[PDB]
Image 1 (tube, one colour):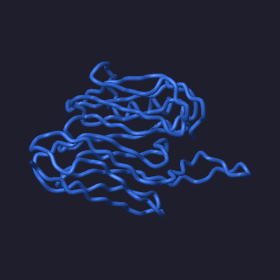
Image 2 (image 1 turned 180 degrees about the horizontal axis):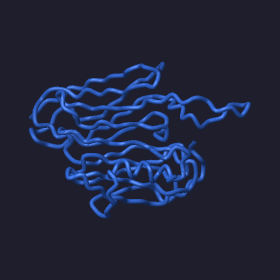
Image 3 (image 1 turned 90 degrees about the vertical axis):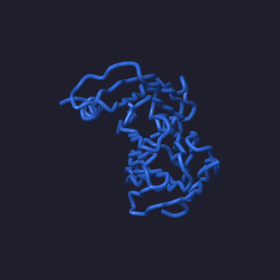
Length: 108
Length: 112
């Protein structure tokens, strides 16, 4: 899908072993499959169906997403930062697209 | 035949019962706009938390699977609710046991 711009908010460093809050947003219509067009016909589903956040290649959270997640899906969760490197955020579209964002994080 | 909520719940529990306690489900008493309702779940120790919306045409909302790099087992998102209904959170622990929390959200504008 077009214009699936990710936005992530997460501190850029942490003390080793500290928790950080991660907030991850992407722009997406998330057409649910329940909306009817002007002629009363259902409009086919097309959503982001999965979101992952990995820290230094290890999973923080893996979310299976269904049509009841809102337009512009938003996820917030907490990562333990034991060592420097990077977060990788991935969103999987029903249409086959894969959206990614990478954010560095340093330690102390 | 069982309800869809019951079917999803049974798949998650492996047929065992749901217990109570061990999790928090936070949702507004009244959601002005059912297109976007903030929900937070917390379940210390959970390997996964599944969210259901029992009055939605397709009740499954999302399943959060916590990996090794999660600091704790909190997640927040925003969801759609078609009308006033109960929202259900199920949390599964490392031993396979499941706990349940449920709360009613009143909805003004429908979100499906």
